[PDB]
Amino acid sequence: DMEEDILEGMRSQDLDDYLNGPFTVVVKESCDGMGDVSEKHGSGPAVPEKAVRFSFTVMRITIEHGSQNVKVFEEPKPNSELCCKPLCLMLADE
Amino acid sequence: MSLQMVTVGHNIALIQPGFSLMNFDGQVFFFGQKGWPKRSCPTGVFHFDIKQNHLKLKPAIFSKDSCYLPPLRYPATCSYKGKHQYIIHGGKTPNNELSDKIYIMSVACKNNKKVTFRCTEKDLVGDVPEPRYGHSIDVVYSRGKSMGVLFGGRSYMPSTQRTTEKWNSVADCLPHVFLIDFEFGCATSYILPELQDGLSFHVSIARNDTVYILGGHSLASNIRPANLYRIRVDLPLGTPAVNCTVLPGGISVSSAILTQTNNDEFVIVGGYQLENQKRMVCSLVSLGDNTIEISEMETPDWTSDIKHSKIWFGSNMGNGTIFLGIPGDNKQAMSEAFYFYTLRCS
Ligand SMILES: [Ca+2]
């Protein structure tokens, strides 16, 4: 999904636009709760219903050209909300 | 046939489906708590004392030279009275792994109203059975020598046929019979042509030369077979010998709880009749020298909560008393998630 961003990454560091790997992809791992999600309109407090997700984040991407590593991608807003891709969702208590 | 409600103290949450109730000299003990061993009670076992129908759960420490054990959520436990000690094997740890150790549980000092267990472990050699849950273990004696039987339960797929789209799947273990030696950890498996399919959650009664494997649930066919078995065995000085017969008059019963009412007389209280609905009527089994008789009893009166619930679970305390458990209805939204009763046979 981040195709053009990795190509513009190696253009901006002035490598070839065509290059085989290997790229090393440093990936952040995170799992934390989500508190409440109950949609009980009114009547009476139906129940709690705590849910929790499992997620990750493509933090940075490096490559080397023979001898030296070079950073072709760095994610600018790391602990954001737009870049925390969901992997698993469950309606289970933490 | 006298149902009685019991109330629980403050550590009510440690009861989960699949506990174990050990018995030692008329005293009861709890095993298989929830989560891991906490900060308060480091071992996992507990005193299950009931007085005036308001139970408590006091801890119970271990010995100096024991082996601290993970809480097993569906093991096979038998009473091996040869001293007095219980035998735990296999089970299901909190990480949903399946352990493969034999755990031997005995008392080392009971005084000043405080006990001290001496849980040591034992490993099997020979035909080591693959780790499983839902199975049952029993000891038999012959020629002045003791031997333990072990029938198959159910377990995960092996390390080849297990992919992560179906990582938590289960399959019935191979229906052999194992003969295990508690003296030296020797196990020799024997395959029986009279035994066809795997079995899980059965009831196992032993009288000194035989095991009455009644009921049990079939997974690969998804039925409950009504074929009560009888594994008449024999132990010579040289090689051991096993035998089984197929008998008529079994009942479709799985995950029912077996307890001892009189000398050589046992009772069966409700497991599951079909997969969707429940089992309400209870059964009485009386043994003999060579015979086996099952019989109905007088259907003890249930509360409307039991007659409306979908599942229940429990074990026996040993003195002809079954302890069961009902999950509380979340539709009322005011519950402690597990109501309880106790069942006095007498
Ligand atoms: Ca949080």
Image (cartoon, rainbow, N blue to C red):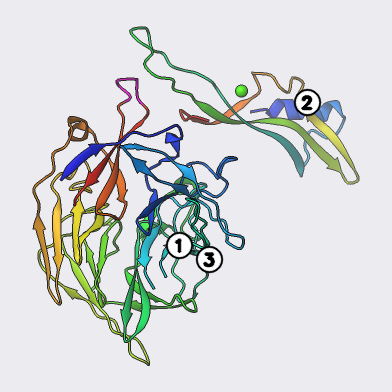
Residue furthest to the front in view is B112
* Residue A13 locus on image (x, y percent): 87, 29
Distance from the alpha carbon under mark 3 to that under mark 2? 62 Å
Both labels 3 and 2 in a single chain = no
Q: Is residue B173 visible?
A: no
Q: Is residue B102 left or right of residue A25?
A: left
Q: Give A40 or B102, whichever is nearer the viewer.
A: B102
Q: To which residue does mark 3 refer? A: B121
Q: Is residue B29 left or right of residue B99?
A: left
The residue at 85%/41% (across/down) is A64
Q: Is mark 3 within 8 Å of ligand 1?
A: no
Q: Is residue B81 left or right of residue B70?
A: left
Q: Is residue B164 visible?
A: yes
Which kind of residue does numbered mark 2 sit on?
Answer: Glu
A89 part of magenta stretch: no
Which kind of residue does numbered mark 3 sit on?
Answer: Glu
Q: Chain of mark 2?
A: A
Distance from the alpha carbon under mark 1 to that under mark 2? 54 Å
In this rendering, the answer to whether B9 lies above or below B334 is below
B331 part of magenta stretch: yes
Q: Secondary structure at mark 3?
A: strand
Q: To which residue does mark 1 refer? A: B131
Q: Quadrant of ligand 1?
A: top right
In this rendering, the answer to whether B92 lies above or below B237 is above
Identify the magenta region. Answer: B330-335
Q: How many callouts does the rendering have?
A: 3
* Residue B129 locus on image (x, y percent): 44, 69
Q: Nearer the viewer, mark 1 or mark 3?
A: 3
Q: To which residue does mark 2 refer? A: A8
Q: Secondary structure at mark 1?
A: loop
Q: Nearer the viewer, mark 1 or mark 2?
A: 1
Q: Chain of mark 3?
A: B
